[PDB]
Amino acid sequence: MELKDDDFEKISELGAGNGGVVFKVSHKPSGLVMARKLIHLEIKPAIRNQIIRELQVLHECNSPYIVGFYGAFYSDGEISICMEHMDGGSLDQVLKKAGRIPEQILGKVSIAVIKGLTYLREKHKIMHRDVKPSNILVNSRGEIKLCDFGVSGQLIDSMANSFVGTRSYMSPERLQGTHYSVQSDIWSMGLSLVEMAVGRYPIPPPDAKELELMFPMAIFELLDYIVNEPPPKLPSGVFSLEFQDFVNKCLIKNPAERADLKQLMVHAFIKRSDAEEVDFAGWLCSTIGLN
Ligand SMILES: Nc1ncnc2c1ncn2[C@@H]1O[C@H](COP(=O)(O)OP(=O)(O)OP(=O)(O)O)[C@@H](O)[C@H]1O
Ligand SMILES: Cn1c(=O)c(F)c(Nc2ccc(I)cc2F)c2c(=O)n(C[C@@H](O)CO)cnc21
Ligand SMILES: [Mg+2]
Image (cartoon, rainbow, N blue to C red; front, side):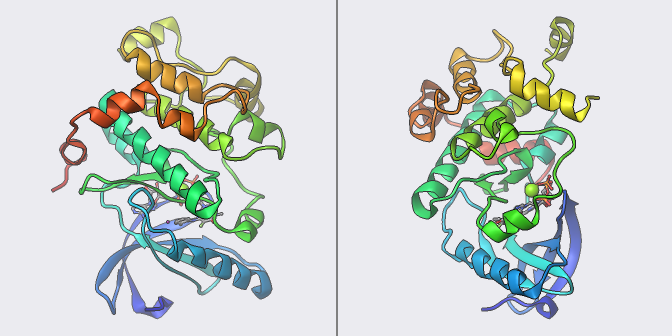
């Protein structure tokens, strides 16, 4: 069935970012619980019809690594996108509580992210454009899923003005110009894994002293660090060398030299992690407190 504003009822607010707020809602006619994301745009009706039009391709997104989609519409000045409610929230929220995320678990996260990007490229000819821990959602069934990928050109265009004035997961090439594509997602995945693995945004790297204890920056300063100074890496010894190599292959500054999805799919770390027996669902609930 078609979704519309009056058929919904707010339960609670799940969080907000730059340019969007997300509610946990009840869709009254079905009784289903959903996550309704609102993007406040005031923009000419002509193009906001185009946006809703372009967003309908998410009905063709069926994948165990992509958040389910229920529908998209326009309301009182707001674009609504209604997704599956992921009761374990995002990986940035999970890292927040967990402090630091185990390597074995990150292994399963990498598999989900890799297969996720693969589906999007294969079945839809699109890159993600915003891979970061807040955009990898998990739930009590143990499923790890991507959302907030860029399906609509007009939306991408209509949002270009804002962005994050700190912490960038953008690749060096994206920061420097318009010449980027799927490879740029590999960089963001790499950076996200390092963050989750260590427990804080990895730029700048920790001191020798900050490291042993473990185990603000200005905009141009941070960006200049991403572009010119050597990429971040996993501290030696306390992560397997397969995992270190894995992130190293993701964090190569040159997009063509950098590993791609097909190569990462067969990396020793993924191959090791595919075999591993991990109660992800159990680890999730036991850390963030669910059932
Ligand atoms: N489908 C969902 N199920 C459960 N929680 C969600 C869902 N989608 C988003 N959220 C939560 O809502 C919050 C806000 O999401 P939103 O995508 O607006 O911004 P963000 O991903 O936090 O950061 P940014 O705005 O910079 O992209 C996220 O932190 C996430 O925890
Ligand atoms: C271009 N684009 C999009 O095209 C887009 F679809 C987006 N959303 C989206 C995509 C897939 C699924 I499943 C659920 C979503 F909410 C999207 C998006 O969410 N964001 C994030 C901001 O709203 C921050 O709050 C940015 N661009 C999006
Ligand atoms: Mg987001």
